[PDB]
Image (cartoon, rainbow over all chains, first blue to last red):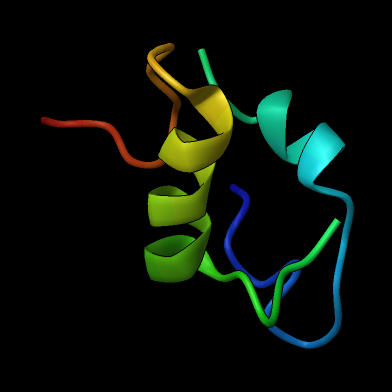
Length: 21
Length: 30
């Protein structure tokens, strides 16, 4: 899955958009 | 960009703020 990957620093809201549908 | 800690709960609310209107994939039913 994709849970523990940002709450321990800061990823890139961009790749975050790739977490959508 | 600005963001402080993102995990499931915070990654979903931001995901939607991110996804704008597009849905996402966090958990599946059964």
